[PDB]
Image (cartoon, coloured by chain):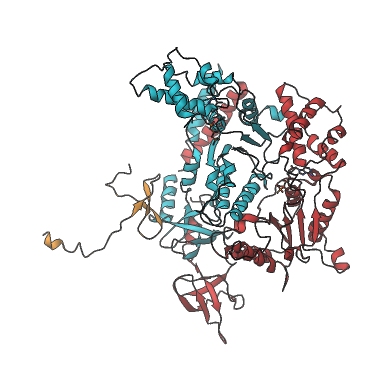
Amino acid sequence: QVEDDIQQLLKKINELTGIKESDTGLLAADKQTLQSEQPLQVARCTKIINADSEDPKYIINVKQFAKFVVDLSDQVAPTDIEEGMRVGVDRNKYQIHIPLPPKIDPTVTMMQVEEKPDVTYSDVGGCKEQIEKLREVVETPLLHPERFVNLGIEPPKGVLLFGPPGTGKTLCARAVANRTDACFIRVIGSELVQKYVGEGARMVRELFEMARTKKACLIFFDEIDAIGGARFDDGAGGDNEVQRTMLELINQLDGFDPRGNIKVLMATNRPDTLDPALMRPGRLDRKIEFSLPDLEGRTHIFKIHARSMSVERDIRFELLARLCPNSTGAEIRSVCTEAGMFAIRARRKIATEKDFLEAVNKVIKSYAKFSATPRYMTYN
Amino acid sequence: LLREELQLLQEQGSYVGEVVRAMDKKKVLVKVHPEGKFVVDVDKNIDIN
Amino acid sequence: LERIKDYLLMEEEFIRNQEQKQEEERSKVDDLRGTPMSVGTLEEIIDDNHAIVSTSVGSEHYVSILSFVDKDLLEPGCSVLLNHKVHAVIGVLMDDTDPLVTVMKVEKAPQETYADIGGLDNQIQEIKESVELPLTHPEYYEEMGIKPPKGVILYGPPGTGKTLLAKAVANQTSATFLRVVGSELIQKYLGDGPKLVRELFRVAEEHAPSIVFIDEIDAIGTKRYDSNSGGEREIQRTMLELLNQLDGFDSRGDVKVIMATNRIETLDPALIRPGRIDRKIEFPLPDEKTKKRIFQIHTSRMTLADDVTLDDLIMAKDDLSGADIKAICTEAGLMALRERRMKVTNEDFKKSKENVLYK
Ligand SMILES: Nc1ncnc2c1ncn2[C@@H]1O[C@H](COP(=O)(O)OP(=O)(O)OP(O)(O)=S)[C@@H](O)[C@H]1O
Ligand SMILES: Nc1ncnc2c1ncn2[C@@H]1O[C@H](COP(=O)(O)OP(=O)(O)OP(O)(O)=S)[C@@H](O)[C@H]1O
């Protein structure tokens, strides 16, 4: 009341007090500058075919209009007007002014990440060797090109990941994407499936355009089974456009002037229908895999999901881990959350051991008819 | 005098266009015939309603 | 007595909210702008306050901007305002409106509430505690720091009330409802599945807290169509896109997802893992007690002639659902208004029973 009425009086006193400046002072924040931008130029952009000899004498296809032979203006450099270069050309006299970056196909612009999702390395504990190897590949050359040069090696420019579903692949990728420091570029595997023939090829072209422009970047591939796994050939002509997309992914990855400062991470759920051209190292070098957390892994993942929740700390966690022999971290998360939900049945602020036992026999033994991994452990 | 008003035919032409929907500040949005769209003005005589 | 001073100062703040030369500056902005404001299309943005646009024919221009409106409302694939004489960026255009949104978003209070559901009482509290109590009462979860359960699968034999449960959640709500039947993910063009999926969840994540209800999704695998490209090797990619869109990257957000099936054993279990979907709920054919509630409520608004017994109808079919009950309770009325009557006799139910069941 007193805070409310006094804050209303003070804030509206400042408001109605500046109202004197509002009704007394009589956009223009740029108006004179914008009218000095009226002697500027419309500057239509184009595409260059070739140059001529002894003179500039440049040749240009605009985009649709025609093709013209032009000359350069005086405020240009006679060097960086090379072929296949989107340059801004005068509308009246048809003269080249500024070279620019090329066409990027803007539906490919929206897969750079532009943010950082907050996932810390602490969330994948119990997978120490995998974290170690993937750290060794991804983090270390971008932050320390010291051991890799003074000993004279090349780090493995590609790492694939696999395992059963829900094992931490996506989560490890996001953990890298927190501490990446590079131009991390997401690619869903279904992004390369378009209506028209050979269009996903051009998407891969533009991906590696962006990759070669910006040095020291990361590209993440995700569920590469849609991108293409096998070249089953019959008298039907079936899955073929996907196959050409996969081949164009092969060649512009690694071979005949290799890739540069780019690292590719792939992640699949079923690494078994893959053409062994991808299985050739030099493209996909380290086969890092995620098995199930055996015994102590689930203790540690209980420590992960349990460290910031309202429980009774007098209980143990090892007995909880001993009842989950073939289980993923997702099922662990469901156990923790569902034990909380059983605590919401009553009105308590701390869990009990019986709540977690209800959670175990609620998740595992009940929904074990679905359970997602009796037919992916065999990697069908 | 109506026949001597023939300097009216000799002036210019006029377009036919399709309205998507209007907006604030006494304007509309018109997609003329083959081309794109244009935020244009009304005359004095027509209702925005 | 705080009402007087609080109201006076709050109305002063509201009138100073409307109190935000100046008309000369408006006229100067109108002088900079042309009157035939032409519409363009961005392709890229260059940081030096002039960028590339794209006209409706394909011509493209490096044009400056009349920078008073927020240019950072604009991305690739946006609609701008341009001039005829200098082609310069006049400013931002508000977004085009909205066939996918208007089709896929249920706007209205969409039917009856929990007073119509027939005796479940346990499934109801589960979907309640998974959607209603989280969203409408987001205070318990702060106390324990436990994230709400994400996905809910409704399943069971046909006629049990999945559609009713979805409609009842959509009744008592505070969030934007998004309904897509799962059979609309099979297109006769190649590469149209992921476009639908990304647009659907783009709508969901951009608009509001929401409930995306996706019904009869099991028919996406067990129904091949001649009006299609290469079937299973596109359907699988569509399911994979739905998978990655559902539990992929970049901080998923405030989007609830409820799906409903008839059969569940023909599903790819990669959707059915937790982390995506946490609650799986069975809908069985109930009992011979909550049937009394179903016949009662579906006869609660009619001039029932009291010479009938509902226990004559409960015993009739051993595995009848609420579908059969609605069918009989409406077909008896159709027999009633066939002969210009109001009240419904026993032989009406007999003919309705012999019409619904055994034909
Ligand atoms: N080893 C783990 N330790 C801790 N949390 C884990 C672990 N594995 C999985 N989780 C949790 O469960 C979630 C599911 O893992 P994800 O990697 O997202 O699954 P996934 O990689 O999408 O598997 P798919 O379906 O084959 S793509 C993670 O985001 C974590 O929240
Ligand atoms: N438990 C119930 N109590 C009352 N009416 C019910 C019940 N179950 C179904 N109904 C009736 O059935 C109609 C709703 O149909 P649903 O049972 O939801 O159909 P459905 O089998 O779920 O269709 P699907 O989802 O494609 S299998 C309502 O109009 C009700 O009259």
Q: Is residue C188 or residue A127 the one in the foreground? A: C188
| Residue C296 in the image, given as x and y percentages of width and height | 51, 18
- Direction from residue A182 to residue C258 in the image, left or right: left
Residue A127 appears in view: yes
Ligand 1 resides in the quarter of the picture at top right
* Direction right: furthest residue: A151
* Direction top: furthest residue: C306
Q: Give the number of callouts.
A: 0
Q: Residue at x 71, y 25 (%)?
A: A344
| Residue C93 in the image, given as x and y percentages of width and height | 47, 50
Where is C327 relative to B42, above or below? above
| Residue A6 in the image, given as x and y percentages of width and height | 59, 25
Task: Say which quadrant the N terminus of chain A sits in.
Answer: top right
* Direction left: furthest residue: B1
Which chain is represented by red in the image? A
Quarter of image, res A345: top right
Which chain is represented by orange in the image? B
Residue C145 appears in view: no
Where is A330 relative to A174, above or below? above
Quarter of image, res A295: top right
Q: Is residue A110 or residue C26 the one in the foreground? A: A110
Where is A28 relative to C117, above or below? below
- Direction from residue C337 to residue A282 in the image, left or right: right
Q: Colour of chain C?
A: cyan
* Direction bottom: furthest residue: A54
Q: Is residue A288 or residue C10 the one in the foreground? A: A288
- Direction from residue A227 to residue B36 in the image, left or right: left
Quarter of image, res A182: bottom right
| Residue C115 in the image, given as x and y percentages of width and height | 53, 21
